[PDB]
Image (spheres, coloured by chain):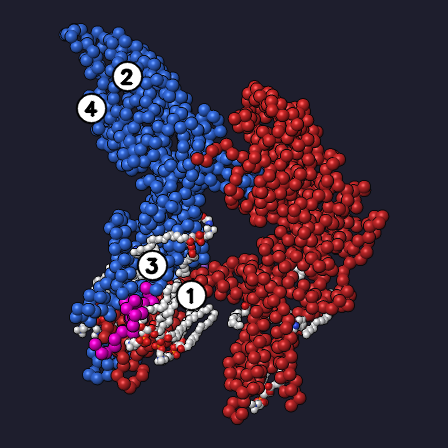
Chain colours: A blue, B red
Amino acid sequence: PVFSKPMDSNIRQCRLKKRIFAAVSEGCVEELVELLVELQELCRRRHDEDVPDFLMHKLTASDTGKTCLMKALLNINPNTKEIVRILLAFAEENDILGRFINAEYTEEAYEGQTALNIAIERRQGDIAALLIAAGADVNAHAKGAFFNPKYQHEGFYFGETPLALAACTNQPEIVQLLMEHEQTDITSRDSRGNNILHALVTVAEDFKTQNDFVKRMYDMILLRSGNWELETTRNNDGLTPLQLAAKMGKAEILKYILSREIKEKRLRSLSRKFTDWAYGPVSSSLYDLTNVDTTTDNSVLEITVYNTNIDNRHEMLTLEPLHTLLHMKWKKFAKHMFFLSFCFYFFYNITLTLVSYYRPREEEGWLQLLGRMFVLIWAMCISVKEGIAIFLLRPSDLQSILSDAWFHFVFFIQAVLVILSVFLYLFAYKEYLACLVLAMALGWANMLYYTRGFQSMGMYSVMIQKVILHDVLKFLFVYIVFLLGFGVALASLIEKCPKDNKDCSSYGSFSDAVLELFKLTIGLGDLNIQQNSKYPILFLFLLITYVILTFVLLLNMLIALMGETVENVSKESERIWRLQRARTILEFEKMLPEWLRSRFRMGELCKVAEDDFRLCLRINEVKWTEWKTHVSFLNE
Amino acid sequence: PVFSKPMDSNIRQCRLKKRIFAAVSEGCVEELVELLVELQELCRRRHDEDVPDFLMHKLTASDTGKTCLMKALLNINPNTKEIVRILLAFAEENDILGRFINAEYTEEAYEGQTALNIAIERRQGDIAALLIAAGADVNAHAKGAFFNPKYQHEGFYFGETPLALAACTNQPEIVQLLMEHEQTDITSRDSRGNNILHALVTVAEDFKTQNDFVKRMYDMILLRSGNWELETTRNNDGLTPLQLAAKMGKAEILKYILSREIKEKRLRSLSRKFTDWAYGPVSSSLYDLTNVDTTTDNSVLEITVYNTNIDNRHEMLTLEPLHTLLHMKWKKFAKHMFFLSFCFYFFYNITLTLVSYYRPREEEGWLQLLGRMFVLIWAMCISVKEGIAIFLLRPSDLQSILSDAWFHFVFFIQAVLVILSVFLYLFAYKEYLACLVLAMALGWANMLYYTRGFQSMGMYSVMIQKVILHDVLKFLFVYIVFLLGFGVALASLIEKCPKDNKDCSSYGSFSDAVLELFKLTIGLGDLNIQQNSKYPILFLFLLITYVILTFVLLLNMLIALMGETVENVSKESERIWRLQRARTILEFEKMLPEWLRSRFRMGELCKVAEDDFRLCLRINEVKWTEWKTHVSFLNE
Ligand SMILES: CCCCCCCC/C=C/CCCCCCCC(=O)O[C@@H](COC(=O)CCCCCCCCCCCCCCC)COP(=O)([O-])OCC[N+](C)(C)C
Ligand SMILES: CCCCCCCC/C=C/CCCCCCCC(=O)O[C@@H](COC(=O)CCCCCCCCCCCCCCC)COP(=O)([O-])OCC[N+](C)(C)C
Ligand SMILES: CCCCCCCC/C=C/CCCCCCCC(=O)O[C@@H](COC(=O)CCCCCCCCCCCCCCC)COP(=O)([O-])OCC[N+](C)(C)C
Ligand SMILES: CCCCCCCC/C=C/CCCCCCCC(=O)O[C@@H](COC(=O)CCCCCCCCCCCCCCC)COP(=O)([O-])OCC[N+](C)(C)C
Ligand SMILES: CCCCCCCC/C=C/CCCCCCCC(=O)O[C@@H](COC(=O)CCCCCCCCCCCCCCC)COP(=O)([O-])OCC[N+](C)(C)C
Ligand SMILES: CCCCCCCC/C=C/CCCCCCCC(=O)O[C@@H](COC(=O)CCCCCCCCCCCCCCC)COP(=O)([O-])OCC[N+](C)(C)C
Ligand SMILES: CCCCCCCC/C=C\CCCCCCCC(=O)O[C@@H](COC(=O)CCCCCCCCCCCCCCC)COP(=O)([O-])OCC[N+](C)(C)C
Ligand SMILES: CCCCCCCC/C=C\CCCCCCCC(=O)O[C@@H](COC(=O)CCCCCCCCCCCCCCC)COP(=O)([O-])OCC[N+](C)(C)C
Ligand SMILES: CCCCCCCC/C=C\CCCCCCCC(=O)O[C@@H](COC(=O)CCCCCCCCCCCCCCC)COP(=O)([O-])OCC[N+](C)(C)C
Ligand SMILES: CCCCCCCC/C=C\CCCCCCCC(=O)O[C@@H](COC(=O)CCCCCCCCCCCCCCC)COP(=O)([O-])OCC[N+](C)(C)C
Ligand SMILES: CCCCC/C=C\C/C=C\C/C=C/C/C=C\CCCC(=O)O
Ligand SMILES: CCCCC/C=C\C/C=C\C/C=C/C/C=C\CCCC(=O)O
Ligand SMILES: NCCOB(c1ccccc1)c1ccccc1
Ligand SMILES: NCCOB(c1ccccc1)c1ccccc1
Ligand SMILES: NCCOB(c1ccccc1)c1ccccc1
Ligand SMILES: NCCOB(c1ccccc1)c1ccccc1
Ligand code: NA
């Protein structure tokens, strides 16, 4: 990144004020005392009306706003605490201690950063305790391009508050010192709208390491708060800390929140998992479904399934209510809607076939009327439905067209070519055969959409798409190099044939020469040596050189590259069809009306505590492997 | 799973009795004393004839049968023992202690569960000792759908007795407390017929982990019993704990039982392995063959070989008498019966060939009579023998048709088509050639059955079957998509040819078009551009698009998927032919008569102890690697 002005500067890029910053940096105590006396006497020699203002302009930098207190804290030495006790005592007789401890940068990239923001970051618990006990602001919002970047490489976002700075830098002794302070606003929201619990989700990691202080900071702040105000708070985008963990793909944080159970009464009401009974490996629990089920707009189940930015959707959709809601919707409507979508579309491809095969060749019942009117209606049903999904779609397709958004185009292109064949055939035109045949060939080719979501057949549609997009299209630029180079080369040697006998040279034009050289590449060629040219040996040299390069080397090079794609999909094949069915379920739920979706709703009302009635889900879990390993070491 | 009623419930799904259950749960001692006095005085205000009955209806739940003693034990707190001592003393002055400690659930899914079943499961050795010393039933059978499920995901099966509950949950201090109790029936059988040693086999694991308490519970209960009553006990299916370990595939338990040797006299008679002498790496032992050799009906060797449900047959057939009986039967009859089965069937395929090749073309010795009568008899011998094996076979073929039950059909189908060709040729019909040729081609194709069971040739028959069933048939649904789509597409562009010259377009029909498109896929095709249509460029576009998809992409995609199958069989190839020969031996033993099987019987009578004469087998084992590692650390 770049900021065009440093935070601290001690190297110059090629007199009372400049010596004070050169005294608080190295740690010269006896020099700093002699310099402050020279500035204490320099207040009254010309005026006594402006004492509190003139004392501040000689201790602050006029370009950044950095004070002499900030300069001592940016440069940590073992003589640091002695400098702070002198500078805070110097503002006592001048009565300027109120504005000296609450100063901030006036520069646009570090605006709002105070001396308390530096002392907590340098791990100075004794110095930060002296500032708060003197009048430092515990609610100072450090804005700016450095503290509020646009990406995670152009600064450092922690939450803009001193409570979020100690929480993100693993310092719980300062968090306990700030939460006991009665002027600290815990539920404060920064420029992003994030509170103390949104900012911990942002700095969290995606997987489980050895030390997880973010989960420890999440539990410590939430239980000492003792309310739901930090959890129901939404951002400027309208996201809770539960929904933010699903958006950014933090599976360890999303697992902890969504099965949080507190056994202690006076603290039990802050739970989302409620175990009813347990007997060995069998447990019965109640799970909160407040923002999880798809009854609100931006629900957690809708985020995780449609989150193409992240890599761990299979880890997050295995979690504790998310796998059961996804399974119960399949056994109620989504298996029925997938079977009928197969049946109405397989009947649609047969009717396209039997009107394309039995077309009126030269001369130009109730079941025949039932067939052709079904073609005109079902093609308009797809072109409206798939046309909305393309319009409601963003142009950054590198992550959505993996297996998902590729089918939204080919069902739409096939539906338009059926409709375009109607306008051509009826009016006056003969180009209907060019549109009806290509729609029928693409119509049968779209039957591989119904192989998706199954353990045995789900990986075949991914193998076809990933070979085309990642192996074949990047290999056309290697092969057209040799197809167009040798194509003009062999066509230039062919002499103009004497008048008759058009089968005297197959390479007699550039359009001819590309055809046979494509046949030598795939192996349907002919090494003809008749070939009436003035250079028979030179034609025979470049013809065999083409066969060795394309057929022997470049053809088997592509097969070795396509074979690496097939084995990579086959290793991930158990994770593919589980993510294919998960998107198929939620698209079928959006096709349902409101009166029918209300019958399909899961959940029952519970009595958690006094004035607490939330929507639950009873999930009977049995864990044999986790039980046998648990019992074994209690009696080793 | 689902049970529609919980064991314990503390969350309500949206007055003297209800306060007692709300007193024993949290642990309020001073509240519970005040509530019992209010119920002690509420016995005599309206009648004194029904004291023992009315005292029980106010302390038990009328819907499940759960008492107040069970409610305190389901909710473990540090104030648990104080509640139990009050409730057991409360039943003393009322003289209702006999029916208060022996109560059970009246609900159909938890019937028979008592307070002793809960106290042992919650690890309360002090509370369970107070119940047994007061009159609790140590032989209470906890039946129900939860405690007796149908699968291992719909409950928790442990053995239905309190002795089996402490044994399966790794609690030997309660097992020693129950086996010293003189009213405890150790040889009790539950609803499955399982005893204390069958139930440990059911909860056992298939492989060797770090901690194996199941083997420790098996040894501790059996040696303190001191008899063979627990070992000879059979289930409702007729299974000993030795035969149950072979049925469920527990190799660690089946290894421990089948080489159990106790060196201590007064305890030596409970052994199955008897070491005769040992000198360094060479040892001579005698192994018990009571239910192991194939002289009883449901023997251990017959179970393990024919156990297609399990994955570790190679680990279990390597064990200590099972590998020697399998090897001694091969060197006595099974190598001779496999060689003659090769010779009588190779002579059968030659005679089918020489009557199919030298058939009467147009006009319609003793060795010729010997040949054709051998065909009529040997085809009836296979059709009777293989017809019984199909009839005695279950329709769940996903695990038996791997390499084993596939040959029972193709020897039968080949034998019927020989017999069907006799009825067609003799009577009046000319369809004998359609049955004799397909039987002769399948007859030579069944010669790969005799490649089975050999280290160099055994894996080839598995590679052919696994490629067809797991790669090819799941790829037809990918390819008929492109074969039927482009087949009608290219046939619809072909104009009806002017009258003569049938070789004007090869795609002139749908039956024609499938033939050449199959030839372009395998690589025997032709990119003809003559092709008299009204769309020569549009025909040429879809023809090359078919070649790039099928021949270049989809053909090499299948080869990459078939190549993963070949390398997976080649890695498991040493485990395949050892399991192929093991099934070949036991099928040849069933073909033997009783007088000839008695000559082939292994074993000699031994004198183990007084009144103990069992059938042995002397196996001279030498273990060089296990000896050199053993001696090395005794003198490090
Ligand atoms: C303009 C356009 C408008 C469109 C109108 C639509 C909009 C309005 C719609 C309204 C519909 C209303 C909702 C549906 C409610 C029905 C309830 C139901 O029975 O569902 C059931 C399915 O029932 C079945 O019969 C499934 C049959 C087997 C499917 C096999 C999948 C393969 C499909 C072809 C793939 C071939 C692959 C080969 C290669 C390609 C749910 O499943 P289940 O059976 O209950 O689960 C068993 C569990 N249980 C029984 C224990 C509970
Ligand atoms: C997944 C998809 C896979 C498949 C998709 C692949 C699809 C490829 C399909 C290919 C089919 C090609 C058909 C050709 C049609 C005619 C062309 C023509 O007119 O040429 C003429 C000139 O011929 C020349 O001299 C060629 C010069 C072209 C300059 C190339 C620059 C751009 C190439 C950038 C590449 C370098 C980039 C480098 C980066 C590494 C010859 O004309 P004619 O034949 O004699 O006509 C007879 C005239 N008459 C009719 C009146 C008698
Ligand atoms: C209606 C239908 C009725 C059916 C009637 C039947 C029912 C009644 C039946 C009654 C039969 C009675 C039982 C048999 C007793 C014989 C004893 C015997 O000698 O056995 C021996 C076999 O000796 C041999 O002769 C084996 C010859 C080599 C075989 C090689 C295997 C390859 C076979 C072709 C594969 C080609 C693969 C190529 C690719 C395809 C046992 O072996 P061994 O030699 O002893 O072992 C050496 C150990 N020792 C010598 C140290 C001890
Ligand atoms: C291990 C095993 C591997 C090998 C086994 C593979 C074996 C495959 C073998 C294949 C050989 C095929 C031979 C065809 C025989 C004739 C058929 C016919 O009559 O067609 C007629 C209509 O033609 C059409 O219009 C086709 C329409 C059929 C509808 C398809 C629906 C079901 C497909 C479900 C698939 C989608 C499922 C989607 C799931 C993803 C054309 O007839 P004709 O030709 O003009 O006849 C001339 C008439 N005359 C004689 C009087 C002159
Ligand atoms: C999946 C992997 C893809 C890539 C790998 C590829 C390999 C695997 C792919 C396998 C796919 C199989 C494609 C076969 C092509 C059929 C051609 C055809 O139509 O026959 C003929 C039709 O003849 C008939 O009318 C009667 C039908 C006989 C067809 C028997 C073919 C074999 C069937 C299954 C064999 C099972 C073997 C199982 C072995 C394990 C041709 O028609 P015609 O006679 O010329 O026209 C007559 C004119 N008329 C119109 C007047 C009538
Ligand atoms: C990269 C991997 C390499 C190794 C693997 C190989 C596989 C991958 C390789 C792919 C490379 C593709 C090479 C195709 C060769 C074309 C031949 C040709 O020129 O056509 C014809 C020209 O016809 C015309 O005049 C109009 C052009 C139509 C050409 C359409 C061909 C398919 C286009 C793309 C299909 C997209 C399918 C996408 C499927 C995913 C032949 O000419 P002619 O008619 O005989 O001459 C007439 C005489 N005249 C001169 C007077 C005019
Ligand atoms: C998986 C769930 C399935 C969902 C529903 C699927 C069910 C779909 C079932 C039927 C759909 C058809 C209804 C459309 C009505 C119009 C038909 C038409 O065009 O006329 C044709 C009549 O039909 C024939 O005679 C064609 C015979 C070959 C058909 C091959 C059988 C496979 C397709 C069907 C079986 C598929 C079974 C699938 C499995 C059940 C024209 O033929 P013609 O006599 O020559 O007329 C002379 C015209 N000419 C003068 C120009 C020459
Ligand atoms: C890949 C794209 C570029 C292709 C290579 C370009 C690079 C070339 C660079 C330099 C070559 C410079 C010399 C060639 C010029 C004269 C040739 C000549 O006149 O023909 C002669 C012989 O025809 C031949 O067979 C000559 C051999 C071809 C030369 C290739 C060099 C070897 C490189 C090998 C590496 C493999 C290739 C690369 C693979 C990694 C004449 O014979 P004629 O025809 O019967 O005519 C008789 C009439 N006359 C005698 C009066 C004439
Ligand atoms: C591994 C253990 C081996 C087990 C036993 C195997 C031993 C098998 C041994 C013999 C089997 C034969 C017994 C059946 C008797 C009937 C034959 C018949 O149909 O008549 C044929 C006579 O025979 C010939 O003339 C055919 C000559 C070619 C045979 C090729 C040798 C390979 C098979 C043999 C050697 C395999 C050796 C295998 C290794 C020992 C008809 O021929 P024809 O003269 O043209 O008659 C005119 C008819 N016409 C007028 C219609 C044209
Ligand atoms: C896979 C199954 C589906 C196959 C594709 C279906 C999707 C298509 C979707 C949309 C296509 C919409 C436009 C086509 C309709 C008009 C075409 C036409 O009239 O022919 C013209 C040229 O013939 C051609 O060569 C045109 C090229 C074919 C179009 C394919 C789009 C490119 C996709 C590439 C991707 C590779 C394919 C997919 C591989 C991943 C006319 O030429 P003529 O014949 O000589 O007749 C002359 C007389 N006339 C001028 C008066 C007419
Ligand atoms: C507006 C039209 C623009 C031109 C058309 C471009 C692209 C659409 C046409 C074809 C794309 C798909 C072809 C199907 C072939 C192989 C994929 C099999 C299905 C799968 O993936 O399993
Ligand atoms: C009642 C008849 C029904 C139709 C017949 C269906 C199936 C039997 C026919 C053929 C099956 C086997 C064919 C042999 C081809 C390859 C396998 C090689 C032998 C092996 O596996 O090593
Ligand atoms: N069969 C259990 C596999 O889990 B499923 C699953 C697991 C992870 C991610 C997505 C789905 C599942 C499959 C179908 C319907 C509902 C859930
Ligand atoms: N909207 C018109 C067709 O939509 B359906 C549809 C079409 C293609 C792919 C997926 C869905 C459909 C959905 C449920 C039942 C039947 C058809
Ligand atoms: N050659 C020793 C291999 O062990 B054999 C074997 C090992 C494990 C499982 C099954 C068999 C064996 C092979 C043939 C006959 C008897 C035993
Ligand atoms: N039962 C009629 C043929 O059976 B035998 C058989 C046939 C096919 C496969 C396996 C065995 C047979 C067995 C031993 C010796 C000779 C033949
Ligand atoms: Na390879």
Q: Which residues are magenta?
A: A348-372
The mark nearer the N terminus, 2 or 3, is 2
Q: Look at mark 3 in the image and give the residue it sits on.
A: A468
Mark 4 or mark 3, whichever is nearer to me = 3
Judging from the image, mark 2 belongs to the subunit labelled A
Q: Look at mark 2 in the image and give the residue it sits on.
A: A101
Q: Main secondary structure of the magenta part?
A: helix
Q: Quadrant of the N terminus of chain A?
A: top left
Q: Is mark 3 within 8 Å of ligand 6?
A: yes
Q: Which residue lies at the image location 58% right of the left edge and 65% below the top edge?
A: B405
Judging from the image, mark 1 belongs to the subunit labelled B
Q: Which residue lies at the image location 44% right of the left edge and 29% below the top edge?
A: A609
Tell me if A230 is positioned left or right of A361 in this view: right
Q: Look at mark 4 in the image and give the residue it sits on.
A: A63
Tell me the number on the disc at residue B200.
Answer: none
Tell me if A545 is positioned left or right of B24 in this view: left
Inter-mark Cα distance, 4 to 2: 19 Å
The mark nearer the N terminus, 4 or 3, is 4
Is residue B289 or residue A466 the one in the foreground? B289
Can residue A394 be seen at all in this image of the molecule? yes
Callout 3 environment at 10 Å: few (<14), some (14 to 19), or many (20+)? Answer: some
Judging from the image, mark 3 belongs to the subunit labelled A
Tell me the number on the disc at residue B476.
Answer: 1
Tell me if B371 is positioned left or right of A318 in this view: right
Callout 2 environment at 10 Å: few (<14), some (14 to 19), or many (20+)? Answer: many
